[PDB]
Amino acid sequence: VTLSIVITVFVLNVHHRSPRTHTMPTWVRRVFLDIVPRLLLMKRPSVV
Amino acid sequence: TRKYECCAEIYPDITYAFVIRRLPLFYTINLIIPCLLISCLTVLVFYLPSECGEKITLCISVLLSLTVFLLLITEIIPSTSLVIPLIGEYLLFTMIFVTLSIVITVFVLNVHHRSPRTHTMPTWVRRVFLDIVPRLLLMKRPSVVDTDFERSVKEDWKYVAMVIDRIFLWMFIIVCLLGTVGLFLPPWLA
Image (cartoon, rainbow over all chains, first blue to last red; front, side, top):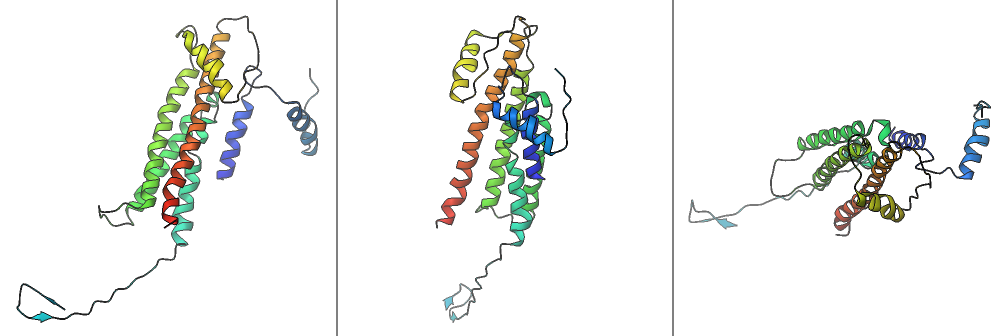
């Protein structure tokens, strides 16, 4: 549960990032928006 | 053998010295580790974004937990005032620093919620907390220009809050590690 608290702090930090403060690395984009979502059977909607 | 003020003769005695050692696996499982786990959450408040609105909840809970543990230990150890347990020292110092984090976190929250309609950014703040300090902390602000004035200064205030947060995240980690090793390593190395 303590480990989950740490991970939740990190996830909250990630969720509240914007281009005005952080820049998205290309590897983060690739991995976490192409590979992992497919494996976890979660599909993002194709919107532009 | 020794002489007492009662009587003029020598009264012998035999003193037995029982040197006993406690097996430190019950109180380590039940007091130490639960104390350490809470102490691990002391620093996370500085990595929590202000917009989440949970900073105060995290540090307040940590403080009220460490306080409870100190009282539980207070009911085990004798009330003698000659020496202080190492566990008592560590808990107390963490409580002092957790309290310091609450004060800092309150101040950081105030900085994050400032806009031109209420406050004015001083010239040197823009120089120090947006140009110099971010470079040192290896956090680089993306180069973005916003036409709006009350969304660019408002966003600058938010970034200043993050920079102040990152300063103490580094400082507390150093202090937390130095304090722990600087307290429990001396005894281990008799």
